[PDB]
Image: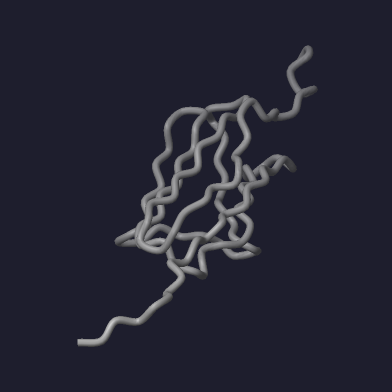
Length: 106
């Protein structure tokens, strides 16, 4: 066992805030110094799980997170933590709402 243990994952590509509006698609991609690694997406402190809308794809050392029907509740803080390591990314999801002004009658 030589220079085998010593080592710690790294962050090649981090995630940046994503500005989206109601009924939109939010995608988050990153790059890690490992392909056999795996983590989960956390929103404002909540385990993000895939659904009929949300679609998570795993590609080598790259993670993807799709979010259909963007809601005003998705906005917060998207942090990904690769199980096994202590690393973590930082990304803020900005939710834009279509302000309503000048009501029309008829």
